[PDB]
Amino acid sequence: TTALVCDNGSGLVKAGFAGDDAPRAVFPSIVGRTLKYPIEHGIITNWDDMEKIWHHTFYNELRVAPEEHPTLLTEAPLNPKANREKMTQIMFETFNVPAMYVAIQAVLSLYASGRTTGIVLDSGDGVTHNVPIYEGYALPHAIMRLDLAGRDLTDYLMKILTERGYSFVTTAEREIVRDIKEKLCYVALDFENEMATAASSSSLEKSYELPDGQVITIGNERFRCPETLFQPSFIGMESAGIHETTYNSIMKCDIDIRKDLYANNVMSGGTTMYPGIADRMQKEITALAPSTMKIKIIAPPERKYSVWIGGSILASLSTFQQMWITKQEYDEAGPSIVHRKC
Amino acid sequence: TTALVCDNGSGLVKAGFAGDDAPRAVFPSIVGRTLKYPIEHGIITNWDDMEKIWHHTFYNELRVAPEEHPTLLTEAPLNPKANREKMTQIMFETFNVPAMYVAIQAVLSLYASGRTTGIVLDSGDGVTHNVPIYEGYALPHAIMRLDLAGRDLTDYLMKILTERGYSFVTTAEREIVRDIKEKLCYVALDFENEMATAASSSSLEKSYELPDGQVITIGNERFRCPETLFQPSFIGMESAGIHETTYNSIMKCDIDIRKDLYANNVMSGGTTMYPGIADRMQKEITALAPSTMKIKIIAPPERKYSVWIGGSILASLSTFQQMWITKQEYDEAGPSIVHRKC
Ligand SMILES: Nc1ncnc2c1ncn2[C@@H]1O[C@H](COP(=O)(O)OP(=O)(O)NP(=O)(O)O)[C@@H](O)[C@H]1O
Ligand SMILES: Nc1ncnc2c1ncn2[C@@H]1O[C@H](COP(=O)(O)OP(=O)(O)NP(=O)(O)O)[C@@H](O)[C@H]1O
Ligand SMILES: C/C1=C/C(=O)O[C@@H]2C[C@@H](CC[C@H](C)/C=C\C=C\CC1)O[C@@](O)([C@@H]1CSC(=O)N1)C2
Ligand SMILES: C/C1=C/C(=O)O[C@@H]2C[C@@H](CC[C@H](C)/C=C\C=C\CC1)O[C@@](O)([C@@H]1CSC(=O)N1)C2
Ligand SMILES: C[N+](C)(C)CCCS(=O)(=O)O
Ligand SMILES: C[N+](C)(C)CCCS(=O)(=O)O
Ligand SMILES: [Ca+2]
Ligand SMILES: [Ca+2]
Ligand SMILES: [Ca+2]
Ligand SMILES: [Ca+2]
């Protein structure tokens, strides 16, 4: 009688029960044979492996029988119709869930901010999306996708620390650098100024303690790493930055709702957790938009879990109860019911 | 009967004869006891040493008897009255010149561009000035001085190459790095973009051959070095950059002539020889000025020698012949004649 909420990400699975303020279980989306990531850039690409992960969610992490709880899952924006159907098939026929639904992650994040209209920036471990949303529906022609997120940043941080004399190379060491990224990296309001402070003084330098007790210093790397979000060619990508893509996204929208989009930039996901990221987005967006445009960036403290929380909220909504797909419905109709409904 | 033109700089002496398109002699402003630079930041600070240099100019470089040629000398903008008088005293009483004059360097550069009104940027080896000029006279309340020029850049280039694995440390090696600076450095139109090209590809890398035959590669250093002109805090200076100081200089001027200043940015001196420096000044000045402002940067090809050439031109002008101070005048009046005249 309690709904489950399962948020499948490229790097982390967020799972728990609808009606809770936070997921009870957060764990890595990996299977080992060497580690495989069954979710690449927000999309499921190995189904056997994904089954093992959902099997782990039910029986190990949450400790519930799947056939007893309606289950709300999440999908990346622009997730192919065929992918969504396979997900539905696995849930009802492998796991015997009594009901389910598949929600778009970035919309859930918007709901968690107490909003139904806005433009979300959702940046995770494997993909970055700009998702314009009007009255609860994502506008698919205007969604932007950037294949650059936290894992790319971490690798970049491994590369640039190497040029300071450190040798971070192994996949175990990649975990240590992810940790440094999360404790020590921030977004410079102005990249040049920051490089010049760091060139001429030690005021931005931080110490980090390694597992074995050794202490190292990191400098301009702190902000050079997440700077790649605004200038992706730092790792050889031609794409525009997250500021430009927010702008391009808003511009693919009907002029009537663009003011509301600009006033409602919601940030979502672990890779939007960099201190200073909101002030830099404000400043960058300002520079591209018309002079009179009211620009607002909302960055909730709990935005590592926004998608999950939006799910918890939706699953609990009286209005949403009519939208669950029941096993009866599915076994009667066919995997198509996941259109004229979801 | 031929006038001499002697342009005394922090690093190089430019000397020759009025009526010529170029100085016949260019040589370093040094005395050795260890090398001393008798001119610090454009100002003469050792007089015995300066006498040796002028003695070298007359007898070794130019091969003329001083008592036979009117001699035009140059001074930094804002050169103290007392300094100018000592110069005059040495010329007439140590060297027995039959006539002389002391001209402001940055005005000469303006004249060499065929102009009497404009704002000069004069950047040498030891000092950088912004000099607003209206109808032939420098406006002293509006002159900006920056203690950052080519020698500072070269040292900075020695420091940053060291962090790439090279060890440029000795004063002999400092000459090699000055040479690299002059053959290989340029000004990025956009610093960030350039850092990102250089981080992700080898397309800005250049080879340089050392005297002993070894070949080295230099990368982002090419534009990181002269970038210090626009962002001086890269070497721990709080001053504004050459773009900001041009702006601040123009703003200390009467509103009536500011349009003419903006339309007439003349660049002068070796440190304005960086490829791309004119486009970057255009762009930076544009960003600070009002939207409607006609901005123009004039960068003559011969601007390493503009000061000298302006001197050659002035010394040859029929209008200027009344302005020479003769030895007769001086021996009659006193070193003050260098006001109600010069
Ligand atoms: N404080 C922090 N600062 C910067 N990055 C962080 C921080 N905390 C977590 N992250 C990054 O957030 C990423 C995972 O966040 P999450 O929003 O769960 O992505 P996900 O859903 O697994 N991947 P995606 O499929 O791209 O949505 C990892 O790369 C983390 O390193
Ligand atoms: N192609 C070039 N690119 C960059 N810098 C250059 C180039 N050629 C010469 N320079 C620099 O120009 C400086 C000397 O130029 P110059 O205009 O003669 O200065 P100066 O009069 O001796 N010094 P100052 O007293 O500051 O005017 C040296 O630092 C050179 O390295
Ligand atoms: C606290 C934590 C957060 C996390 O996000 O882990 C996820 C998943 C993790 C799986 C691989 C490691 C060995 C398995 C152990 C995990 C413990 C959870 C680690 O690989 C990431 O590190 C990748 C690699 S480097 C990066 O930036 N993303 C993201
Ligand atoms: C072609 C050339 C140009 C020049 O500008 O020399 C001047 C004067 C020079 C004097 C010291 C050396 C050893 C003496 C030899 C000179 C030959 C002329 C050198 O020291 C500079 O190099 C300084 C130091 S490093 C720099 O950036 N400015 C500028
Ligand atoms: C304000 N902001 C966090 C963006 C920059 C501060 C740099 S630091 O954290 O003090 O090193
Ligand atoms: C155009 N400008 C000279 C400023 C930059 C070109 C860089 S490079 O000389 O081709 O390496
Ligand atoms: Ca996610
Ligand atoms: Ca780019
Ligand atoms: Ca000079
Ligand atoms: Ca500064």
Image: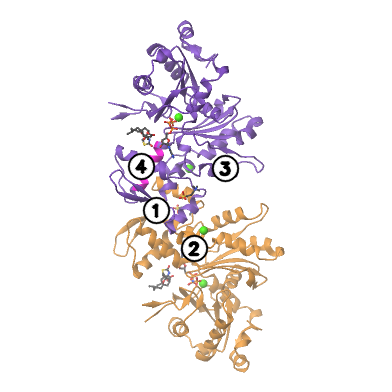
Chain colours: A purple, B orange
Q: Are marks 1 and 3 in contact (CB under 8 Å)?
A: no
Report the Cα–Cα distance between label 3 and label 4.
28 Å
Whether ligand 3 has any atom under 8 Å from the Cβ at mark 4 is answered as yes
Q: Amino acid at mark 4?
A: Val
Report the Cα–Cα distance between label 4 and label 2.
33 Å
Q: Secondary structure at mark 1?
A: loop
Q: Secondary structure at mark 4?
A: helix
Picture coordinates of residue A248, whole percent (x, y):
56, 35
Instruction: Judge depth for marks 4 and 1 and give the one in front.
Output: 4
Query: Dot 3 corresponds to which residue?
Result: A282
Query: Dot 4 corresponds to which residue?
Result: A177
Placement of B291 over or under B146, stated as above or below: above
Query: Dot 1 corresponds to which residue?
Result: B219
What is the span of residues highlighted in magenta in the rendered image?
A151-161
Whether ligand 5 has any atom under 8 Å from the Cβ at mark 3 is answered as no
Picture coordinates of residue B220, whole percent (x, y):
42, 53
The residue depicted at 49 percent of the width and 34 percent of the height is A302
Which quarter shows the N terminus of chain B?
A: bottom right
Residue sitting at the far top: A332
Q: Residues within 10 Å of mark 4 (few under 14, many from 20)?
A: many
Q: Amino acid at mark 1?
A: Gly
Q: Amino acid at mark 2?
A: Met
